[PDB]
Length: 107
Image 1 (cartoon, rainbow, N blue to C red):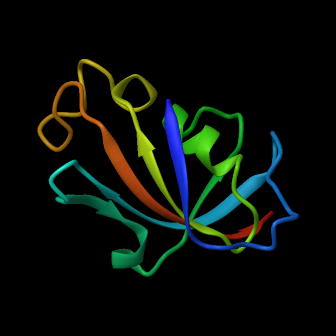
Image 2: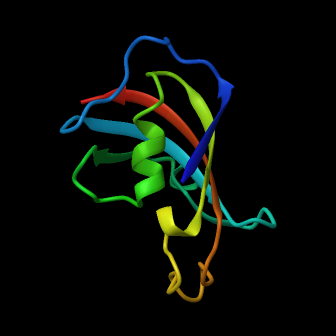
């Protein structure tokens, strides 16, 4: 599944719902800390629609548990990420992923 650990608190009140668009900054890392992707490096927040299945399951279910303004560490099992096949060569088979996610706003 996905484990959500707070880095810094959000408002504690505004949680995203299915169909809403979330705006986030994120960094994705493998278990040894290697970064594989980051919106901060592009200086461009990332948007996705909750429930559209346009991101991996853990990032979706994890952000659903975040409030606006929160920054959190999401640890995601491979079955909630890229599974047995992965995303070669950047994501190996059966990889647990760690994302640092900041929920900036809902649209």
